Length: 88
Ligand SMILES: [Cl-]
Image 1 (cartoon, helix red, strand yellow):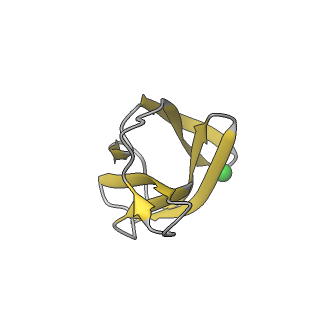
Image 2: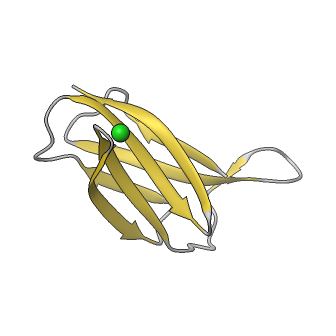
């Protein structure tokens, strides 16, 4: 499993992509499994907002959040992926 956030740095909308790494080719697949997951937006060791979706591609609204250092965390089937995200 892989997490990609675009663009970098974050504007009002961050596109999150959760692709499956194909076990044969090693290429990134946009899977039709569409399993539910949770996206958490963290800053200063506080979970500020969360979103729940089945879409591997999701636009995160960062509206209302000030400029600074954030962490985006995906919780999917027990597995977590966390990435530093700078909001300008
Ligand atoms: Cl944090």
